[PDB]
Image: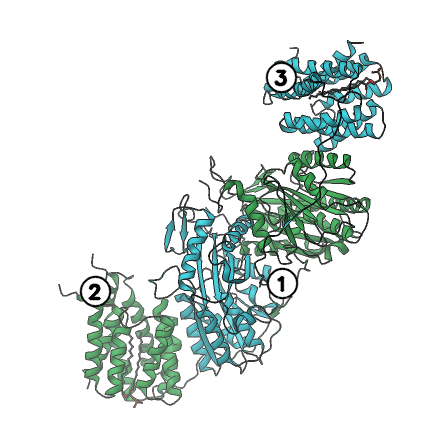
Chain colours: A cyan, B green
């Protein structure tokens, strides 16, 4: 039932911590020696002269909170087990470990377990002479009737402000004051299509509503505030924006954080970002934080939108650089500029011209392929889609038509090939059309460089092989074409030899035919056969 | 069926592009004016004097490739629909739009659709005089028997090297040479627990093998090379490391990229990072790229490991700063340092002392609670877990025992309270224990500041409320405690009044009792009742 990458369940959180450290951009993180049941990460920049800002809580919201430890933000983070509050002992240990006379501010997300455990910790700390303050963050607005708003993504915006002042030597009282001020100006709303996968065997797959979306699903998977009858990005985001606007002051600039709860695709997150930029909330946004996975719920497929009012010191504090593994640098929503380029008409130019010889070839090649439609479909039907005959016929007739309408530059092969190369893909769908267009386009160009027909045709083959990836023996027209083009390269005028070569190659494709679970002529590749018949026709006209 | 955030299916990719631009860190991205069916993103830093490096392919791998467009990397990216190759027209348009005499290098992931479409494009470009080169990247090693290795995450490492040389004015030939050299030294292997959710109605949920993992699942959800009978992070990573080692040179330094296909939790990604750091591959790693979502498969819950050999110019080129939305700065795997702190024994010190008065109170309070065990469980059983009586009895007896063993500092309330506060949570499990410990700890400290008992008890209540979050009327012991403590604050010695107050409060909890779907005494909160009986006992001893 467990769909989770992990090793020993009991070492889960510890392993996450090791990984976070191993990838530390600043290499400013360090575990704190302690009993295995205490999981504290602290910064190596320990400057007890400044006020310590400690945070934490149950794990499963990485990069929170370890990812926000460092200069300008969190001093330490107390990590509980997955979605489980840290022990009182653990919290105390962190306080004593990084708190100097300046004191420390505990930033706690609104959840009983954390409030009670960090709380008893603060109390035990105070008895030991430490100066402690606690700020409970409850930024969720999904449940108006809730006495205790849950603390979610916005919490880190609180870390940011608290960190600003703490690093700059302001006193505990000031840190708390400002931190509380930020909290009071932070509003978040989340939505999810499905809950998260837990690192354990469960009773039922993650909660999910088909075609719908649960507004307000908690970061621990808690029941949300409602269910939206659609997953449409615009509808979902605008609904969220309305509720955000109803909670925000009617005026003032805003910073908005687009947080990925863990399971939304980057593509989706981009679309969400676009919706937000087009929402009624748009004209008041001066900064975007994300889209990014900042405060997650394991792999929960949902996202959250956090709006913080930019009053007073808030904005100054948000924009200050810090040194953490995951703080994202705020960015003003950029406008979508549209660049214009100077592109020459791809369309190949030409002037109809006669040449009885060439016309005779074009007519012959053209007819042979056209006549083979049903036979080539039959061969293709064996394993393919039974349409190769029609695809090839489509191209033949297109060039035949142009021929019959005296529209071909028959007197100039280079331009003629270039013209066919341009027209085939338009009438021939699928890889066949593209490959043939590649063939003639490259051939037409080799001729433009003044090469003889056979040389150009071989270059066409060479290019068809490079892009197509096929080789002699893979059962495609190549198996008959190459032999023929090689035959002609030695005997430029011996059409009988060319045909014979192509014919042998086509025959080889009947052997290596896997699909066959007597004469085996029904296992012949249509491409090769078509090719062999073309040369056969050419050889019989000489 | 569709579990995807999007609006109009036909505008999906376009909306993703808009969002990518809106969030552009460098604001160096711009859409290219064109037919709606052509989706090209180009850099505003267009310097046609240098060789252009174009990429792209089907969408759903964000941030690739739009996220690697910029100085030092991609010049432009051609975006097809979700998991569908861009049109030939589209690719050409990009070439003509950003290519100067210096020419351009097309970097294509190994997939027919892309090879054929970028291919015909290159051919049509060459006829127009542009100098073009194409490098097909096939870094996947999951399918040894495959003639055409799929191109996955490693592709961007190729963009990095190509970009290095192109920005520095080297010629096309050199760009291609180096780009090919990087490719040849790039090896990737992916694994997934489930395929991705598509932006459409489907026949069945994403492919998934319960308890197992599909090794080599493609970035388009293509069938992998095998199925691992476990999801264990260590086993899975070591298996992958073996195969990587079998493909890598037996010696040489390495850069390893840990890519999140889109649906793995950040926690999981950290654990994976730890496994890699402990794998036999460990001693040859000088740089880590990620964990991060770099080349995704929508929300596919899997990850990939790419190893690139650091020979010649590779390392120099990897470490150069570039200007893109998502290139991650490589980091040396940090070692996990363990810090030591100086923490004073939390354990409260005391010396047994007598005091008949206090002892009489402790005995009385202690007994009353103990006697009420079964009755309080009965009340708690109504809606709670029916254990409050036992939890409270557990604490009572613990303090009674200490009392009976002449172990209490009876002559010093401050230390006595501090001692009880320390011992309750140890014997009382759950929030009840923590709350009571909070109460006494804070009370003991208020006394230490030289306050009278009633004042200290009120501070205890105040702290219990702050952390506990409960208020008068929420149906907890507070409903009886507060009234009593307030009564005593006015009449310090009138125990009868205190009891009566507590009793009224306990009675109030019988009314607001929701659970009841006569006398209503069975709807009384255990906490409140326990509290009322304590005071009743005190009042009856005077
Ligand atoms: C899928 C639909 C494709 C539709 C293709 C239509 C166009 C067919 C190709 C027209 C070729 C015109 C060749 C012009 C004749 C020529 O080059 O004469 C010069 C040379 C030497 O002089 P001589 O002819 O007077 O003795 O002629 C030759 O060397 C003979 C070689 C002829 C090779 C023909 C190959 C045709 C392409 C086969 C493609 C098959 C695709 C299924
Ligand atoms: C369900 C949990 C209920 C918790 C109730 C706590 C009840 C405390 C009872 C205190 C009686 C009220 C004080 C009366 C005024 C007074 O002054 O009494 C005289 C004396 C000295 O006061 P002074 O120094 O200010 O002049 O007060 C005392 O001696 C207080 C003795 C406290 C004994 C506490 C026993 C605690 C047992 C905890 C068991 C926990 C089980 C979960």
Residue A424, position as x, y percentages in the image: 68, 26
Choose between A359 and B360: the one closer to the eye.
A359
Q: Point out the residue furthest to the left here.
A: B518
Classify mark 2: helix, strand or loop.
helix
Instruction: Read off the chain for label 3.
Output: A
Residue A231, position as x, y percentages in the image: 44, 46
The residue that label 2 is drawn on is B523
Labels 1 and 2 positioned on one and the same chain:
no
Residue A379, numbered label: 3
Classify mark 3: helix, strand or loop.
helix
The residue that label 1 is drawn on is A24
How far apart are labels 3 and 2 at the CA level?
83 Å
Q: Is residue A119 above or below residue A305?
A: below
How far apart are labels 1 and 3 at the CA level?
60 Å
- Badge 2: residue crowd in 10 Å (few <14, some 14–19, many ≥20): many
Q: Is residue B492 above or below residue A337?
A: below
Choose between B474 and B278: the one closer to the eye.
B474
Instruction: Read off the chain for label 2.
Output: B
Q: Residue at x 41, y 57 (%)?
A: A242
Choose between B253 and A414: the one closer to the eye.
A414
Classify mark 1: helix, strand or loop.
loop
């Amino acid at each position: 039932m467990s769909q989770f990458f992990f090793n020993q369940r009991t070492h889960l959180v510890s392993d996450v911590i090791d990984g976070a450290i191993i990838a530390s951009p600043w290499n400013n993180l360090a575990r704190l020696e302690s009993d295995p049941a205490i999981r504290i990460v602290v910064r190596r920049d320990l400057n007890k002269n400044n006020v310590a800002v400690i945070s934490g809580g149950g794990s499963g919201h990485e990069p929170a909170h370890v990812g926000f430890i460092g200069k300008g933000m969190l001093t330490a983070a107390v990590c509980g087990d997955v979605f489980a509050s840290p022990s009182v002992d653990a919290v105390l240990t962190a306080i004593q470990a990084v708190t100097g006379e300046a004191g420390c501010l505990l930033i706690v997300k609104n959840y009983t377990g954390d409030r009670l455990n960090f709380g008893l910790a603060a109390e035990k700390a105070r008895r030991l002479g430490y100066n402690v303050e606690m700020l409970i963050v409850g930024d969720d607005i999904s449940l108006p009737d809730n006495k205790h708003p849950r603390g979610i993504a916005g919490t880190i915006l609180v870390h940011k402000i608290a960190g600003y002042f703490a690093e700059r030597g302001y006193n505990l009282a000031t840190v708390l004051r400002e931190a509380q001020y930020a909290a009071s100006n932070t509003f978040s709303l989340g939505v999810a299509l499905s809950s998260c996968h837990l690192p354990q065997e469960t009773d039922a797959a993650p909660r999910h509503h088909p075609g719908h979306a649960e507004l307000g699903m908690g970061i621990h998977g808690e029941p949300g505030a409602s269910v939206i009858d659609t997953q449409n990005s615009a509808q979902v985001v605008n609904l969220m924006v309305d509720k955000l606007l109803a909670a925000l002051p009617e005026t003032g600039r805003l910073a908005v954080m687009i947080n990925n709860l863990g399971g939304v695709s980057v593509a989706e997150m981009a679309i969400i970002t676009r919706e937000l930029a087009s929402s009624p909330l748009h004209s008041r946004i001066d900064w975007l934080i994300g889209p990014a996975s900042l405060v997650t719920a394991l792999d929960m497929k949902g996202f959250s939108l956090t709006a913080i009012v930019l009053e007073e010191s808030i904005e100054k504090a948000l924009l200050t650089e810090v040194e953490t593994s995951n703080w994202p640098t705020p960015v003003p929503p950029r406008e979508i500029t549209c660049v214009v380029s100077s592109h020459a008409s791809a369309r190949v130019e030409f002037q109809p011209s006669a040449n009885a010889l060439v016309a005779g070839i074009v007519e012959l090649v053209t007819a042979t392929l056209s006549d083979l439609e049903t036979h080539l479909n039959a061969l293709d039907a064996k394993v393919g889609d039974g349409d190769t005959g029609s695809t090839f016929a489509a191209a033949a007739r297109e060039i035949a038509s142009l021929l019959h309408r005296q529209q071909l530059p028959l007197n100039n092969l280079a331009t003629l090939f270039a013209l066919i190369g341009e027209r085939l893909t338009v009438v021939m769908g699928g890889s066949s059309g593209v490959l043939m267009s590649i063939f003639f386009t490259a051939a037409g160009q080799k001729l433009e460089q003044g090469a003889n027909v056979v040389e150009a045709l071989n270059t066409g083959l060479a290019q068809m092989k490079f892009y197509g990836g096929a080789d002699e023996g893979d059962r495609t027209m190549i198996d008959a074409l190459q032999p023929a083009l090689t035959s002609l390269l030695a005997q430029p005028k011996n059409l009988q030899a060319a045909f014979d070569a192509a014919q042998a190659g086509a025959e080889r494709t009947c052997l290596s035919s896997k699909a066959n679970a007597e004469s085996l002529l029904g296992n012949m590749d249509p491409g090769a056969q078509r090719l062999a018949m073309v040369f056969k026709a050419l050889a019989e006209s000489e």
